[PDB]
Image 1 (cartoon, rainbow, N blue to C red):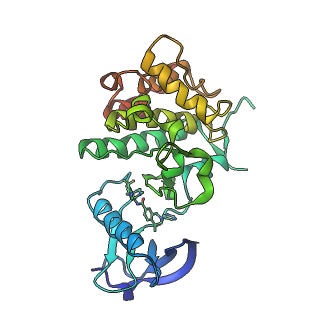
Image 2 (cartoon, rainbow, N blue to C red; image 1 turned 30 degrees about the vertical axis):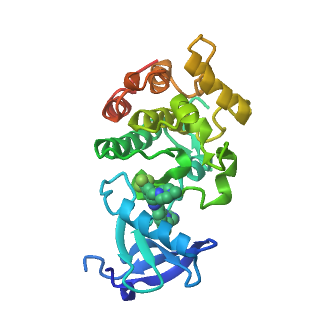
Length: 285
Ligand SMILES: C[C@@H]1CN(c2cncnc2)Cc2cc(C(=O)Nc3cc(CN4CCN(C)CC4)cc(C(F)(F)F)c3)ccc21
């Protein structure tokens, strides 16, 4: 159990109905101070919130990769319940890219095209790790991607904890609230979530990166039309629709995005392939 006496409060990062998130300093992290994010459960939090908290701890404890959020420690042998992760200073990737303009010499901070590819390749690397562990993320989007120092990307999962992105989730039949615009066609129709559908979502995430998070995927189409589109991928009568090529995206890179959106799960490129393309092949028109 992490010694909670080693956590020095600095600033509250956010609040919730069942807990609080704090930015903490740890002096001499080798066991100047290391900054960490600590989720503390309120002493009056529900037994259901406590259940989610402990299961969240279990899940995270297995994920140890440079492009995945790390669980540093937990304080659970006593109350209040704490979970300690890395602190990603630049917030989520949607908030990060939305604050930048593209570096375009032919034409507020700037971000270059090679840097957008490095960001996407780090997301690919993280996902390759999850896929090799048979772990299906189920909600890959830029909002669930965290930005640290040196343009380091760490894939996370906030769920619906932040009310910031309610427009990105749709309540289907059964009170299940899903991110349909990022979901593969088999997910929306059959609830079939696999590594292959994580690829589809990566494809939509690469679109967001290339758009500098300026627009919602299929923004001109209603939620009902995004669902009806998945039925068109099922019928395979050539009437299904794809996200349009971002202005700064070359045709070669757009062709990779379309592959992630193949009708057949087995035709979608593995994360090892996306990673190599994004890190090596940027020499395309
Ligand atoms: C306090 C702290 C705040 N913070 C933060 C970092 N820098 C700057 N400001 C805040 C990052 C962070 C991330 C997580 C997190 O990422 N946790 C997670 C949970 C699941 C499972 N699962 C549980 C249920 N739920 C519905 C869906 C997700 C799967 C995965 C993943 F992605 F790694 F697989 C990750 C949890 C707590 C915190």
